[PDB]
Image (tube, rainbow, N blue to C red):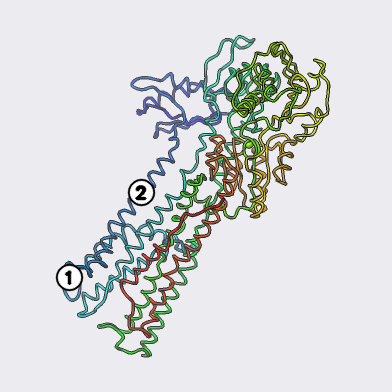
Amino acid sequence: DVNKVHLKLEGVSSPEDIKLIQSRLESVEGVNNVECDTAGQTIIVAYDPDVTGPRLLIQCIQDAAQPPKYFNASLYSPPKQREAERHHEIRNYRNQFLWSCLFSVPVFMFSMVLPMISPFGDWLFYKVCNNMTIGMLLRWLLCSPVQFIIGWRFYVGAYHALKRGYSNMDVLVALGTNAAYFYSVYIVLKALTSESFEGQDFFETSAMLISFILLGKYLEVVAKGKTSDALSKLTELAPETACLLTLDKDGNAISETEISTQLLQRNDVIKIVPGEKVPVDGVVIKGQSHVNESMITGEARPIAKKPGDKVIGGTVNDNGCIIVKVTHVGSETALSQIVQLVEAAQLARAPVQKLADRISRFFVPTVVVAAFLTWLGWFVAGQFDIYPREWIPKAMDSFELALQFGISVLVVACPCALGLATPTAVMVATGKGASQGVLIKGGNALEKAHKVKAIIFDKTGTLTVGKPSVVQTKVFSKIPLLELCDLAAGAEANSEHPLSKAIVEYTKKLREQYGSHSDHIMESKDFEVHPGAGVSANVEGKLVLVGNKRLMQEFEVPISSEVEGHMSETEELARTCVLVAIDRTICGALSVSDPLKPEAGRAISYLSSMGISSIMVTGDNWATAKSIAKEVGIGTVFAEIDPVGKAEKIKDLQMKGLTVAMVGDGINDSPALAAADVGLAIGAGTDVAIEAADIVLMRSSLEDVITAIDLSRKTLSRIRLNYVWALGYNVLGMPVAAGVLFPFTGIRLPPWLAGACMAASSVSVVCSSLLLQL
Ligand SMILES: [Mg+2]
């Protein structure tokens, strides 16, 4: 913005308006450079960042607004265009595969079914000049579009492997169509020239290979996962407008209008009405209010801000309008750092080299050498005349038979199920995971999650807490349990702290635990709110004392044994983990804190059983992090870690190998969630964490992590087996294609049971969805 702006005119289609805008901009001094892109109806304005402001430029643009349109100038790009791009890709691949089927299925049918079928089987035998048949010509004409027109991708892939020294899936593995087609053309031409030549064409294999490879590409695009990602959520987290605050106070006149935050500059002021999301980072001039800092800290404790403190863009205040002088804006904001980390992580994942490409790299030389060896062997055997002469078919020589047995190896040795292996395991894995409640967006997660050795958990909503709540209550004030809850609710009647509200819901839970919520309470008078001490309030004229020993002494309440037993670590000194909550008399207290685990302990134990270690990287107090690490069992723990520090930890672990996986809950985790090998998000968390991860967990459960890892392990199994079965019949029929059978048996090669092993291979590439991981 302040550095360079792409002012795209809206509703402008004539160069005269652009020229008027150019003249108006040149009439204003301060812009370093004006790039005049006449073609495109857009203009680039570059100038020194952190001076003046785009508001003057926008006003100058708006001064030229004339009918029939309104001349708006701001950077227009099509947002969430990757969804439409994914639809375009899906339509393109589906229609191309459908066209390949429309040309291949007739070839296969006319080749294999009609010859055996009832009277319409001699229609594709009616001879032409010499021994050219109607069937051969029709198969040629139908298959020719498939080999060439739809094969442009394959030929350009082969030409892209010109001298680079590699054999991808678009090399002879898929170009065996090129050999089969040319051999079939040779057969047809010779039948046109020869007089008996009882032979058959191989047009089936080319069309079938093209169809299966296009199906593999289509299914790969389908199983690639949900449409990339969406960094737009990070920007949506920032406010779109801000209240300009040149209002009354000394050198500030009246302003209250809402101006775009992107248009705000340094040395500006925003007040943020209570209950508003702060636009940009700043330093407060005056004002006391609590903010829900979660972009950096990640927790939900209301941080109190007094005059002279700072503020982080994205949070919401609740205790009044807090005027703030604007600090660093734009690319220097903390949210900007988070965003930049996100796209740096996104444009750093090199796509995994498909095992199909590796095989084809180490399979084409094998096939070519094998075919050449068969050709040489039969050529030698014919030139030295070992095998009987009558073995050769009519009108053929030894060299022709050698060529036949050589090209047979090339035709049979065609993967034709290699591209169908990974897609038709990833799809089934994703479906079964969605059934189990583990939605896995992207197959890349499927292949990279099996080798995960380290996992990194987060604390403020990932492993421990859904929302703060009370645990481990004991009788206090030497009063009945129901009337304990009576005191609790009576004290809560005037306090509205988030911990106090959690006490309200937990008291309601106790009430319904005693059969049902018994009636209601009396109002608490004298809501003094003693600083430091806590809530002191006359409940029906009786003073409840939710607060520490100072509040005990201000009402002259004694001290007892447990008073020094239940805080610090979590349950060591000050009688309640995060609060005090004694009420009027002393007999005990409660244990308001964050929840511990619904299952997390056994999940971590099972993860350690499989060898995957766990590391905790939180952004909370050291004491709580140590407490949780001791409780659940995580050894390594890091506290007060910003998202940048999380990314650095991921980078260090990755540099030590041991492909990592982060389980995230909120804004704090997103940089590491994108920077890890695979991202895990808790469904109960916020939208940005759901978006930034690769394996979102539908139901909030740590056991979903082990389900995902187990699913990835079982899909890395049943995929090497899929590759084995895809190599399978082809590599086992390579000897049959070569000819080692004709010396022993009488059959040379069944024309139908030569290409009709790819169907068996395709059926053998089938996966069952029975996980049962417990
Ligand atoms: Mg958290």
Ligand 1 positioned in quadrant: top right
Q: Residue 649's quadrant in the figure?
A: top right
Residue 277: image location, x then y, percent: 57, 24
Q: Residue at x 44, y 20 (%)?
A: 62
Of callouts 2 and 1, which one flags the residue occurring earlier in the amino acid sequence? 2
The residue shown at (37%, 60%) is: 212
Q: Is residue 190 left or right of residue 600?
A: left
Q: Is residue 389 above or below residue 557?
A: below
Residue type indicated by callout 1: Asp
Label 1 SS: loop
- Dot 2 amino acid type: Asn
Q: Residues within 10 Å of mark 2 (few under 14, many from 20)?
A: few
Residue at numbered disc 2 = 92
Nearer to the camera, 449 or 467: 467
Please, what secondary structure does the residue beneath circle 2 have?
A: helix
Write down the quadrant of residue 316 in the picture: top right
State left or right for residue 610 relative to residue 405.
right
Q: Mark 1: few, some, or many residues within 10 Å (few <14, many ≥20)?
A: some
Residue 282 percent location from the top left of the image: 64, 24
Label 1 residue near ligand 1, CB within 8 Å? no
Q: Is residue 328 visible?
A: no
**In the displayed structure, does residue 683 sit left or right of residue 109?**
right
Taking the image as drawn, is residue 452 in sight? yes
Give the label on residue 122, or none.
1
